[PDB]
Length: 48
Length: 48
Image (cartoon, rainbow over all chains, first blue to last red; front, top):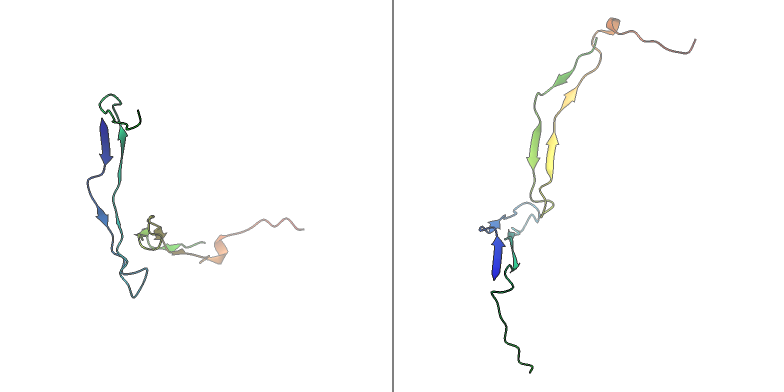
C-alpha cells in the first residue's frame, strides 16, 4: 500500500564559518511517500 | 602589439555555508593585458 521513497543518508554540514562564534550544525534528510496501491489499505470509521 | 597575461586555470570555490540550502560556486580566473608594441596596431578613425 504505502511506498516510502527516500535517500538513505542524513547529510550533515557543521558551519564554523557563517556565525563566527558559533558552530551552526545543519542536518537534512530527504524523504517522501504516499499510497501506491489503494486496494492494499482499509480503514475503520467510527461513524455508523 | 598586444600581450595577454593570465593564469591558465579557473579557481572554483564552492561555498555551502553562506546560502545554506544552496552551494554558491565562487569562480575567478585572473587575466590582464595591454598593448606592448605600440607600433604594431593602427586604427581607422572616421573623423576627417
